[PDB]
Length: 262
Ligand SMILES: Nc1ncnc2c1ncn2[C@@H]1O[C@H](CSCC[C@H](N)C(=O)O)[C@@H](O)[C@H]1O
Image (cartoon, rainbow, N blue to C red):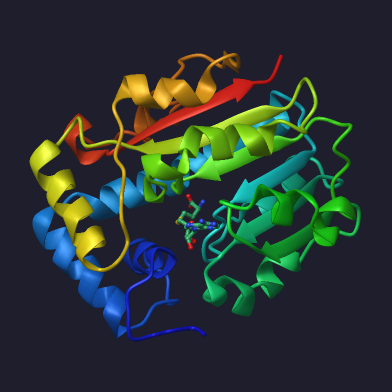
């Protein structure tokens, strides 16, 4: 089931940001993409760094102690639960992915603080019931208490015909007031030619992609209260000292946004 003869998004991602969890097909795809867009590693790294600042924000500033992460990806230190449990050891996290390789490396995701709880579910976000009714999720999270729904660097693989906005809002629906939605949303607006070429490289490798305008990204957050600065390129979302050190706007193809459910 690993299917090493074709490229997979989690593995290309892991290859580009410096992990070992990839195969020849994934390196080949990554290298072809970087040829088209030399800033790919800056962008992919900035996304992963955005995840870290967003989770830190949620855990620390917003006091969220429960996370549901859709499209978890291959584990890479610090993982979301590691950031959340470092602020608050009792924090709970459910990780979810549909790439079989993630399950093989799930031990790192399950390595929780004793006070906290983590779980991993292999499931498709296009089937929210299989996620929401998952025993692993129900034994881990209390849906009557606030939950941060993290949907990071995944929605660009969800085409309009599947209603990405609907799928996301369906997952947020059972979460109570005070919950949050944090997303990173792929866009070609800042480097249309190079990002466009990379998107067609994913499409040519059976990984259809949907890049979005700022107005399309706003659709996900209708009725939710956006945390300032709203929907901005990820390197401009609550940056650290050196978060944008040598990063041009054209080198970042993700919007980042965090919002509270009223
Ligand atoms: N329909 C689906 N259901 C669940 N996971 C999916 C999916 N489509 C893609 N994915 C997963 O989404 C991940 C995108 S990579 C992003 C990983 C992580 N959220 C991060 O931002 O750092 C991959 O691991 C891929 O396998």
